[PDB]
Amino acid sequence: NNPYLFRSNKFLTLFKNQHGSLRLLQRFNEDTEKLENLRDYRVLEYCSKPNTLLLPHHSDSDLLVLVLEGQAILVLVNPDGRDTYKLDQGDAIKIQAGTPFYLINPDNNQNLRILKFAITFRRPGTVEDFFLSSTKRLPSYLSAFSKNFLEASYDSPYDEIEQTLLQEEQEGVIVKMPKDDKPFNLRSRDPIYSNNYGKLYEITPEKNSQLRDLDILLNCLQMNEGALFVPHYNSRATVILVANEGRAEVELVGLEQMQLRRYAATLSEGDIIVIPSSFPVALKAASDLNMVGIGVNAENNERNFLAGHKENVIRQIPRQVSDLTFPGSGEEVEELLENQKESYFVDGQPR
Amino acid sequence: NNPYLFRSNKFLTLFKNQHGSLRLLQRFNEDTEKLENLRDYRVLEYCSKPNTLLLPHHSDSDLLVLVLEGQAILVLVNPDGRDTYKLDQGDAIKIQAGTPFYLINPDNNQNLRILKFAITFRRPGTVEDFFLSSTKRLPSYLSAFSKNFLEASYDSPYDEIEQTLLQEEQEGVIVKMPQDKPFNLRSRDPIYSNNYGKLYEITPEKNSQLRDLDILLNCLQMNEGALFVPHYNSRATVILVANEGRAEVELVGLEQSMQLRRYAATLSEGDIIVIPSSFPVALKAASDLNMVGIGVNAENNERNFLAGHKENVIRQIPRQVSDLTFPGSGEEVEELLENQKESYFVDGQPR
Amino acid sequence: NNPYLFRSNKFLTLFKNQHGSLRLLQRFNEDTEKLENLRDYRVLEYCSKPNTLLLPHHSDSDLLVLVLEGQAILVLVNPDGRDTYKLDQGDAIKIQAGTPFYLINPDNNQNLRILKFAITFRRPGTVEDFFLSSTKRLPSYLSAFSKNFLEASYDSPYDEIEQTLLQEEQEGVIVKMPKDQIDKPFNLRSRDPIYSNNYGKLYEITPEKNSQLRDLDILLNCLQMNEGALFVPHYNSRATVILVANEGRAEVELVGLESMQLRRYAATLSEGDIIVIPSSFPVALKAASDLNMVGIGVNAENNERNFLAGHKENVIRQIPRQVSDLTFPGSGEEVEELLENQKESYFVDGQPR
Ligand SMILES: [Ca+2]
Ligand SMILES: [Ca+2]
Ligand SMILES: [Ca+2]
């Protein structure tokens, strides 16, 4: 059918109560041999109501954390202290594997939506979270040690340790909270494409130290209803495209082991499509839309356009060769390619 | 029967007409578990008659392109222009994934033979080519986009787009013809040169294009009757491609206490043998011969000789220890090892 | 049941005679899908009696070589000459793939015990040895070439080649020595121990501090504990540690997460026994006797050890009162108090109360 399309319903709920939820996308390679280059990566969605705290835990994986909606306070605990960060909409930050952290939605009215990208290394494709808190879904990891180990460790009788640290709590890992390097914004630089129809912002590993270690680019797409992101392809980056707001009509063109395949889907909020490198892709805004792209294998990526005035590789083929490439003449090919005056994003209204 | 040997007949014909052919070697790991270290690599052979053009296309893979015979004009298309390169025999150049390119045989009389080495990353072991031109085998990938997407993109009626770009013009991708440049395998002094043979070798340490791929390229020329004496590579696995003449290869592997096996084959034009790192190998020229070696995992490769005067590791074992290593005496081992006065290449005539 | 535990009996004997032995641990991923991150690595143990020589051979793999007991002379053969190294107890060195070498136990009285860590690249998970010497288990690899190839190569009649290089002389690849006189090794204990109190010491060499370890992305540590001492619950952020019991008996408790579900892996380790400690998994270790252990940490770059008990480097103590109160069933005050009870750091008295 479409091995590149992941609907909101292909997410497993890890935890949910009335205060928020943690969801985990199935392995990219669960249902297809075609995405073995994504086997090390998992996607998570965290959603929390006003005045909520995700209790402290470390992941066995590196995390890229992105605020899709609202605002957050992120605390990273280290062996000798802690670092406290305010995250606004569009703010991203890397959490190093094995750093205990907790996440607060400090807003009194607006929900918090966070996209988490996991880069796994201990057990490729597997993400584990170690929660200090004992809850219905799992006891504290501390509880797995023997009585003698715990008593000697904390120099305290087991009874005190058990009542003070271990006993299974009444809420889960998201609770209501009293008072009832650095983050970087996806839009911290000038957009790389910008006209009356759309904008794309892009942060690359070349320009960002946190993204450099992961070999990842992040982009942020805004388009007006009826705008069309024209046919183009990425030379190196495979892009995990996340629908944030609005509805996107995607056409993806692939070669499969033999056959030429069209992949066409309308994506609503939460929906994900993978755009493999070299595969031509185009995207029409059915409503005003915001989308986030995560590009893996990002180093030295180059975007090649197949329509419009600027960065159109077809326009760069000389008349002599275009004449032999296409049924038209060099003159007819050149003329047709000049008809589109816009670049990158155009009017997608039919005629 | 020799999992390292790939005869010309283990190539699939991807495309062939009266103007030329493109052939693709089976996956190194198709028929053996012994070459998992080569799973990311594929070999292609392109042959074209005089005054031919391979039509513009991009690959999803990095390409090392090497002219085995003749001359080529190579055009690399970028979003803002194009680079044109003359390739002579022995000239190699890396084509970055997603770079549209076309290949002309400008010669009036001599064929063009090209060796293409594919380094895959999107789908390991799979190489895809995206041809702009519609042909009998497959329509243009542009044709896979919807009518509304194409009309909006090119700001032109579908009729004109279809007649100018999309209709099947050529029957095949080979037709009649009306930053950082190629390097020749012999642009440096050969590393071994005597009356019997020469080896030229370009390493990733000395070539910016090879550095990113961790690959070395070597070029072997021997006179009929010359013998390339037993040696092994510490790190590089060498894909050895017979170009001209007939090569008698002896490869020694430790493959089921382990069973010790000789893999002996005579290689003729197109035939490939893989020489795993650490495996002793020798080659006798049955006729005058030329061969090309592609060495992967090339960084810090060191070639250890088991015979001859220079770079002979056995000669470096002191008498006391060689006396315990070999049935001879230290003196008898030292004396025997001094009998061969030549280095690297010797007279291979039967006693 | 415990997929992280490798008893001395999960080693295959590659070679053994009266002079010593070479043993090879089963693939980390032979019996479990949980150790895919260790697929490229193998562990070997070489043991030799006094006055012994392991005959010249190259490996298809990179080798990290560590003297667990006694002393060695290591000779590396290069195309143009040779390098000779003295290795004492706690000395390690990397041997480059394809470098022929020989190993001597020069001591007259003490055995030589060496831990070999193989980093495979030719055939991931496979380590091969190429011996120049013909023995019962295998003829010389030189013998596998045709007569004509050998005669032309050595410019000698096959009879002299065969008598001088090829004939099976030695019974095995470990032989007695008549006379032992006829970037350099580094010691695990060359720096201050990073943890040291009255109960235990840990020494650690990291890729950040050692060029040989940097190219392999490996850290080595060396653990010494007194009977009754306890290495308190902690975890490694990035390094998966292959823990090798050298002397005495260790009681290990390892806590894993494969809903996913919570698992205790408890084992007592005797000499030779190995346990794998995956990164992020809390671990603790009690010395049943005086104990020495060696850790090989892979994926070592930027590893940080987080302690869950004791005063120093205790991540739990760095959670503010307000949040501790919400994290634990106790109150911020009761949590803070309890975490301050243990006055020691890293290693404590493990005696039951
Ligand atoms: Ca040849
Ligand atoms: Ca002898
Ligand atoms: Ca000794």
Image (cartoon, coloured by chain):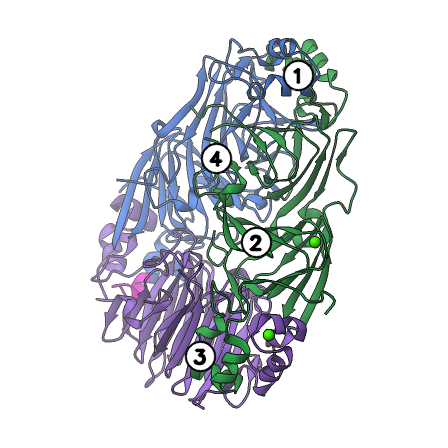
Chain colours: A blue, B purple, C green
Q: Which residues are magenta?
A: A324-333
Q: Amino acid at mark 4?
A: Pro
Residue A121 appearing in the image: yes
* Label 2 in the same subunit as label 1: no
Seen from the viewer's position, the closer of residues B239 and C342 is C342
Instruction: Please name the residue that numbered disc 2 is placed on.
Output: C21
Label 4 and label 1: CA atoms lie apart by 27 Å
Q: Amino acid at mark 1?
A: Glu
Label 2 and label 1: CA atoms lie apart by 43 Å
Q: Chain of mark 4?
A: C
Seen from the viewer's position, the closer of residues A34 and A233 is A34
Rendered position, C199 above or below B30: above
Residue at 63% across, 8% down: A159
Seen from the viewer's position, the closer of residues C140 and A273 is C140
Secondary structure beneath dot 4 equals: loop
Q: Chain of mark 2?
A: C
Label 1 and label 3: CA atoms lie apart by 70 Å
Q: Which mark is residue A151?
A: 1
**Sequence order check, earlier mark of 2 and 4:** 4
Q: Is residue B116 magenta?
A: no
Q: Amino acid at mark 2?
A: Ser
For ligand 1, which image quadrant applies?
A: bottom left
Q: Which mark is residue C3?
A: 4
Instruction: Please name the residue that numbered disc 3 is placed on.
Output: B283
Q: Residues within 10 Å of mark 2 (few under 14, many from 20)?
A: some
Residue at 63% across, 33% down: C249
Secondary structure beneath dot 3 equals: strand
Relative image position of residue A103 (x, y in whole percent): 57, 22
Label 2 and label 4: CA atoms lie apart by 26 Å
Residue B88 appearing in the image: no
Q: Nearer the viewer, mark 2 or mark 1?
A: 2
